[PDB]
Image 1 (cartoon, helix red, strand yellow):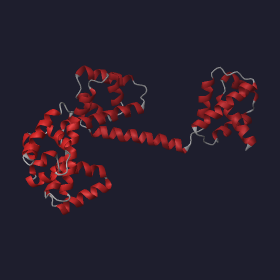
Image 2: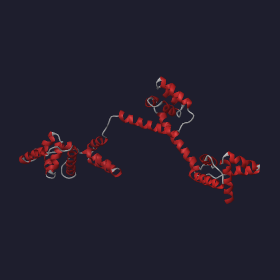
Image 3: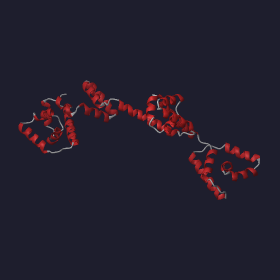
Image 4: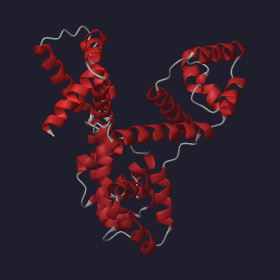
Length: 321
């Protein structure tokens, strides 16, 4: 297809070149010749857009070197892009893009028009018009009815003047509106510490059930399991432990770690540890606690979780709970 491709180039040139150049070509060519060139262009194979640009730029360089002046080279490239058809892949891409925009706007169509009107009313009138231009007439009518009066008139006037709309711009507008609705829903909802709620439930469940649930959660998501277990025994739960349990904890925990942990601890938990030490060890502990001076909250928190890590091993070994 070497002579066929040269003929195909001729066909594309005929249709793409400026009319000053190609009017003379048409006059010299017979009707049979012109029709052979038209049939060649019509029967062209489809070519990816990036490859049509390289073909266009080759052709442009080739005819400039052939001795033909091209005043509007970018208009020549676009004309070649009209002649050479697009591929099935490119047709599918456009279809998929259109389908995604449709899916997004269907989700918008489900949303109460009072909510859409409320989210749209402080937007620029041209933005509201561009958005409403893509909705069903009854949706856009419902939204318009829930807008202020002078905005009803201005949005409809701007819709009236539209000659074009960029689909991707409106799609993006719609997705930001869906995220804003999702964000308002979170603000409308009661905040809930799910890891804590799950922890209480598990602590109420018997060990057989509790441990089998957690193990399965850990296999799929080991980070979530751990965040749940952190809530199952907290520093405040030291109150639940016996004096016997505290003695065993005092045998293992570092003094400095315990001192620091107790700086941000309630008074009854302080006394829970202090009452299980000796008179002199307790007295010296309180004295050294004042000796520390200003300690960061992040460090008090760290020492508290360290005591809890130690306490977990007691639950896994000695201390009943």
